Length: 212
Length: 212
Ligand SMILES: N[C@@H](CCC(=O)N[C@@H](CS)C(=O)NCC(=O)O)C(=O)O
Ligand SMILES: N[C@@H](CCC(=O)N[C@@H](CS)C(=O)NCC(=O)O)C(=O)O
Image (cartoon, rainbow over the protein chains, first blue to last red):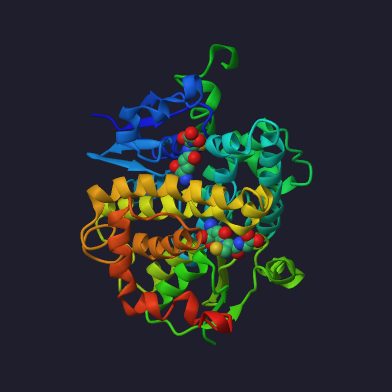
């Protein structure tokens, strides 16, 4: 059977994996998990047995179940090598992983749904904006040394796969991107590639009709 | 020159790297970065040029500067292969990375100093406890399927290197570990190994005298 991705249309972490799967040419099926309706499907007993962390994505592939988007992408990289998400040179690989982790560990978790719920309605917007602006202040500086056409040199990497979904989140939270011209430029360049379009939140099984 | 690690004695993420460096037998120097005194040395202009994200660890090695503890550890794994932080089988590698990311992306960032400062004095303790108990609820369930002597089978891996420092944080935040017998058992087993002792917060250049 085809690999099965458990995804939510609006989920940044899910988008990451959908981009990687498109990049690697892997035909997969999606099982949508609605993260918001009736408290969220991620809390169901069935989904909790799939991922005790109660998050998407989860990928069933090659007879196993993998959670954590970067762990998934590293698995895909090791088993379906081309196109490469990571370059061959260990020093350049470290830079790609550094940027991916800055986003995936340093920004996204602090603006995740469950965290925003704990912050509360009155402060969640400002909180999300602060986390993202702080992260992008740093990332924009780093990209001055690392970026070519893309985040790390001239080939698409895992850092780019993390960048686009986090920038879309920045737009959703009404963050001013004008002080981040390099993030902005690279984001536009990546969005011109088919693998970032076919995988897009507005083209998902579970995209609400009003957003298609 | 020897590799230079920028570290804080109490930093969980720094401990990770110190364990990996000990594991790989790499002789290194530490430059302490005091994260608390006078607002924190991580905000100095000099440290900001080292790491715009204003966090430890940072490692200078082989003529480059790497930030992000998991990116550092993956670099060390690729360049100094034994003892292995990741197993040879891509499916087992995915499990090690999943657990490492659960901790490093799913728990630690939400109990980091800068986040606790934004939560505020009145709520930070309860916040940290909630994040850690939620993460450990999930992790303890996952380890039921994955763990042998250690988090993933019978060889120490990157998941173990992430586990111990996060458990020490759990102790510092007064989290009840009694419902986590597998995390507790594995933690005790790893703490019996020299590489987790030589690297310990209480044996650092910058350990306050009262804690030595
Ligand atoms: N570090 C993770 C985080 C996964 C995650 O936070 N997923 C979000 C969607 S982007 C989620 O399922 N949140 C559910 C919730 O907050 O209740 C990974 O990269 O897979
Ligand atoms: N994802 C990171 C996080 C690094 C991090 O949060 N470091 C903490 C120490 S454990 C820090 O320097 N915090 C400084 C602050 O919060 O101002 C990594 O694994 O290196």
